[PDB]
Amino acid sequence: KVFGRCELAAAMKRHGLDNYRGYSLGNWVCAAKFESNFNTQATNRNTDGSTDYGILQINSRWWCNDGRTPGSRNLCNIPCSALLSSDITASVNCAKKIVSDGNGMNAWVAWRNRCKGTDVQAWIRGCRL
Ligand SMILES: [Cl-]
């Protein structure tokens, strides 16, 4: 599934992500946009064998379990196969798990190099939320 911008914004606000640990909805919208462009199926396998999964590109080394990473922690307790669902609930719960660690949304490098420090509202702008 390739979410619409505010289809995903509404799905994230109905998931309680608005201002979760200090990060307004614009942060999450923009982070998803620049991690996978609103794609739940997206996947990226990086030379160490770990793999970024889902709409938030959660890595398969700390957070999920795919059974083919030699690391390999499963801190969200989840098969990455559930992070590739149409429903974003698994990814949202694991992301609340991650963002509550003290690194914050700096755990997602795309949000850090494109979103962090911007007027992120413009992502939930015109949303009809
Ligand atoms: Cl980038």
Image (cartoon, grey):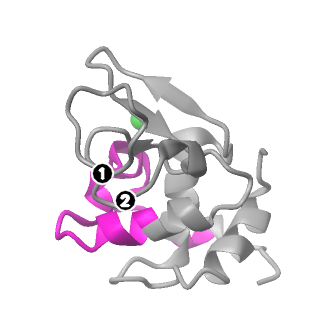
- How far across and down, in percent of the image, does residue 94 sit? 42, 63
Decide which of 67, 88 is in the foreground and name it: 67
> Which numbered tag is attached to residue 11?
none
Q: How many marks?
A: 2
Q: Residue at point 52% right, 59% down?
A: 91
Q: Residue at point 55% right, 31% down?
A: 43
- Which residue type does callout 1 highlight? Asn
Snapshot quadrant of residue 66:
top left
- Report ligand 1 position as a quadrant: top left
- How far across and down, in percent of the image, does residue 112 sit? 33, 50
Q: CA distance from mark 2 to mark 1?
A: 5 Å
Decide which of 118, 105 is in the foreground and name it: 105
Residue 125 visible in the picture: no
> Which numbered tag is attached to residue 77?
2
Snapshot quadrant of residue 2:
top right
Answer with left or right where residue 19 lies relative to residue 9: left
**Cβ–Cβ below 8 Å for labels 2 and 1?**
yes
Q: Tell me the quarter of the image containing the C terminus.
A: bottom right
- Which residue type does callout 2 highlight? Asn
**Residue annotated with mark 1:** 74
**Is ligand 1 closer than 8 angstroms to the Cβ of mark 2?**
no
Answer with left or right where residue 33 lies relative to residue 48: right
Task: Check disc 2: other Cα within 10 Å, few if <14, some if 14-19, many if 20+.
Answer: few
Residue 103 magenta: yes
Decide which of 48, 70 is in the foreground and name it: 70
Q: Tell me the quarter of the image containing the N terminus.
A: top right
Image: 123 above or below 17: above
Please, what secondary structure does the residue beneath circle 1 have?
loop
- How far across and down, in percent of the image, does residue 71 sit? 20, 33
The magenta segment is 94-122
- How far across and down, in percent of the image, does residue 49 sit? 32, 20
